[PDB]
Length: 341
Ligand SMILES: *[C@@H]1O[C@H](CO)[C@@H](O[C@@H]2O[C@H](CO)[C@@H](O[C@H]3O[C@H](CO)[C@@H](O[C@@H]4O[C@H](CO)[C@@H](O)[C@H](O)[C@@H]4O)[C@H](O)[C@@H]3O)[C@H](O)[C@H]2NC(C)=O)[C@H](O)[C@H]1NC(C)=O
Ligand SMILES: *[C@@H]1O[C@H](CO)[C@@H](O[C@@H]2O[C@H](CO)[C@@H](O[C@@H]3O[C@H](CO)[C@@H](O)[C@H](O)[C@@H]3O)[C@H](O)[C@H]2NC(C)=O)[C@H](O)[C@H]1NC(C)=O
Ligand SMILES: *[C@@H]1O[C@H](CO)[C@@H](O[C@@H]2O[C@H](CO)[C@@H](O)[C@H](O)[C@H]2NC(C)=O)[C@H](O)[C@H]1NC(C)=O
Ligand SMILES: [Fe+3]
Ligand SMILES: [Zn+2]
Ligand SMILES: [Zn+2]
Image (cartoon, rainbow, N blue to C red):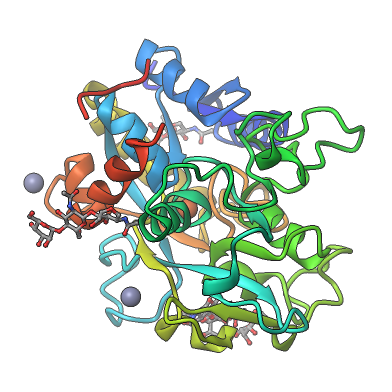
């Protein structure tokens, strides 16, 4: 009865969640929904307990009363061995990536080009770049900025979905889940790699994890970091090695959210689950690994070292940071006392 019901977004996450359920002796069970928003609703209804969310979604969930529980913490050597679970998160770098061969393309010549986004409402893939663009063009018509895009979650018949490809069969074009070929960090980077789009709004880690043999996936196998460039806000282009001096923003880390009344129980179960299936986990590589799914970033990002305890029991606004919260509210003024549900 102590059981935590995880919410999986789409069939692939559902399959991984089921594997996790089996290996956890049903200490974790699965609820599945087609989109992250639907999962948030299941949690609000009490039909699911938790799921790991990108900051843009933490904002949506938070307005609905859901809270931060634990955050993804990426192998980053700083904070010596203050162990992982106790190490404070540093956030990730949201970047704009283009092909080096696409010369002359800069942050200042993005209008009318083709873009690849992780998903509508996500932090590196949407909130940050579109916020910056609405800001600079002084206009809310962000649906008109890029000539075509793949922005999972947007209207499928719109130009924002024109570049999306759907699943092996063309079904689910533009759905905001892994069934869409170009969905998420890896999908948006793939959209760029395959030259479907001119620019990809992802995070620094994505570029590294899908180049120079780091991915053995067929579209990624042959990719070289030097064939890519980051777009700096000052109009310059730099090597992906320059991320720290050429990013759009620093993003909150993805984090597990739950209803406030279930947060303590979810935290407890998760800490026990990663002890078993996390990076150095007792049953990881071996029976199951919570943080692996072949660069597909299912349930959690594949580069997650551990889920870390938060500092000073954050409200969702403290967790996301005042800078980011303001940016989202300002951007959403184009589409304050919320919960869209
Ligand atoms: C941009 O994002 C990348 C990827 O997240 C950052 O680069 C990573 O930096 C980490 C340290 O800050 C490196 O972590 C360790 O990874 C392994 C652990 O075994 C060590 O060797 C590696 O072996 C693996 C597997 O064969 C390879 O993927 C690596 O090439 C590497 O040789 C490594 O010494 C280190 O201790 C991590 O490797 C590294 N990842 C990659 C793919 O380069 C980068 O810092 C970040 N930039 C910014 C500005 O944040
Ligand atoms: C695009 O839209 C607006 C244009 O400025 C941006 O919102 C503004 O963001 C700044 C920076 O976070 C806010 O400034 C802050 O002011 C508060 C007090 O007013 C202070 O506590 C902070 O130290 C900081 O100085 C500013 O308030 C905010 N303004 C309003 C009225 O919303 C937005 O950030 C831009 N979008 C992006 C993605 O950059
Ligand atoms: C399901 O969860 C329970 C704990 O809530 C796991 O079992 C206990 O774990 C502690 C510490 O890890 C052990 O010291 C206890 O003795 C375990 N209880 C017993 C009675 O075995 C339990 O193993 C989990 N189930 C699986 C299959 O992972
Ligand atoms: Fe994100
Ligand atoms: Zn910065
Ligand atoms: Zn506080």
